Image (tube, rainbow, N blue to C red; front, side, top):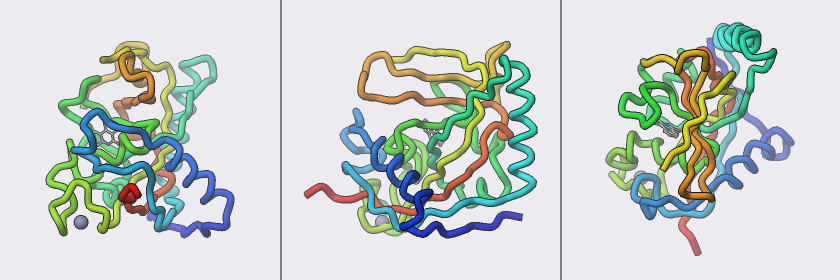
Length: 208
Ligand SMILES: O=c1[nH]c2ccccc2c2ccccc12
Ligand SMILES: [Zn+2]
């Protein structure tokens, strides 16, 4: 079902997506432990993920959410890192991708900071790092993230230092209160509320 289309780096669509990736890198409180030490990425490839059944699953669910929230899907584009991106792009999101120990419950987590999603590319807390070098800060191996269309609907606002949504909500917003430089994180509880739109292949870059 899924087919992947290479975007040219001269295409505006590519550039828009790259810019969203580069401009939402921040520093992490773990000093780079989970995700590596870097200020920027080497973007190697960006692919559009095209799957009819998964798209229609998304848009059908989105209409439902919209109708339950003053005609407002509250659709965002957000990052998702995972060692199972190959399974997500082919079969879509489901409970297997839920973060069971998540601070805002057992749901599927997304980030506004590309660097936050980068922390989960090799598993929770970076796992054991890249398969080839067992290095969480590997500058050599290729990483992949997803840049997804996520339907948030009415989103429970949780300030902060597969389950169900809170009643009358379609998602949760984890908004950092302490780190003012940290962007929001969002959780959904149905896989049908995200479409994995772009697969981004990259390396983290070692700082000068
Ligand atoms: O991109 C993410 N991928 C994940 C994969 C598995 C578990 C948790 C997360 C997660 C948590 C917070 C923010 C972003 C992410
Ligand atoms: Zn490596």
